[PDB]
Amino acid sequence: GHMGRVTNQLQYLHKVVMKALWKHQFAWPFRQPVDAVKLGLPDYHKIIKQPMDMGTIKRRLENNYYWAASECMQDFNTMFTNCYIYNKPTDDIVLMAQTLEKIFLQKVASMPQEEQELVVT
Ligand SMILES: Cc1noc(C)c1-c1cc(C(N)=O)c2c(c1)c1ccc(C(=O)N3C[C@@H](C)O[C@@H](C)C3)cc1n2CC1CC1
């Protein structure tokens, strides 16, 4: 019971935002879902109810899964927040998320302000 589309903001999130974040030095733990068995975190899925990662976001952008840019921005917010709330403040993963979230926020500030659907053939 869901469908997506191509908007100017969603295209910006794919072509500008995801391009800057995907290739970053600190992106590698965020490129695929948190593997709690590999990491030895048996409480992860008890605490985190909505896991999210950049690989899922990228795939969703490529397959036009989102109806609006706000849904994609929520996925980014969830991914960063999951990381901060679950982990210890002294874990380096926290600083890696902080570095990427700062880039994310700056790019969102430069996004075209009004959401419009595009005709993409
Ligand atoms: C994100 C995130 N939020 O909370 C946590 C915890 C995470 C989060 C998520 C993942 C994941 N996606 O499963 C994850 C890590 C942290 C993580 C930390 C360290 C190492 C590690 O020790 N390495 C790998 C490095 C390439 O080389 C070293 C030599 C050894 C692997 C890790 N992975 C595995 C991923 C590479 C596939």
Image (cartoon, helix red, strand yellow):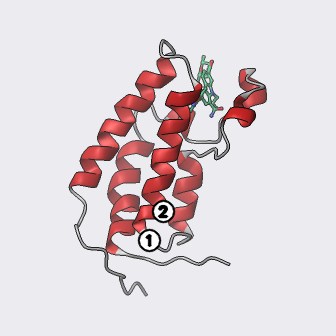
Position of residue 48 relative to residue 118, above or below, is above
Q: Is residue 36 visible?
A: yes
Count neighbours of disc 2 (C-alpha within 10 A) and say few if under 14, some if 14 to 19, many if 20 or more. Answer: few
Q: Is mark 1 within 8 Å of ligand 1?
A: no
Write the residue at 30% across / 40% down: 103
User: Horizontal and vertical percent for residue 71?
Assistant: 48, 62
- Which image quadrant is residue 118 in? bottom left
Query: Quarter of the image containing the C terminus?
Result: bottom left
Q: Residue at x 22, y 67 (%)?
A: 113
Q: Look at the image and tell me in which quarter the N terminus lies.
A: bottom right
In-front residue for pair 120/117: 117
Q: Nearer the viewer, residue 109 or 8?
A: 109
- 8 versus 96 height, above or below: below
Residue 74's x, y, as percent? 47, 54
Mark 2 close to ligand 1, CB under 8 Å: no
Q: Is residue 30 left or right of residue 70?
A: right
Under tag 1, what secondary structure? Answer: loop
Left or right, 25 with reference to 39: left
Q: Which residue is mark 1?
A: 68
Q: CA distance from mark 2 to mark 1?
A: 6 Å
Residue at the disc numbered 2: 71
Residue 35: in sight, yes or no? no
Contact? badges 2 and 1 (CB < 8 Å): yes
| Residue 64 position in % (x across, y down) | 53, 72
The residue type indicated by label 1 comes to Ala
Q: Quadrant of ligand 1?
A: top right
Residue sticking out furthest to the top: 90
Three-letter code for the amino acid on which mark 2 is drawn: Glu
The residue closer to the viewer here, 25 or 34, is 34
Q: Position of residue 38 (x, y in %)?
A: 75, 26
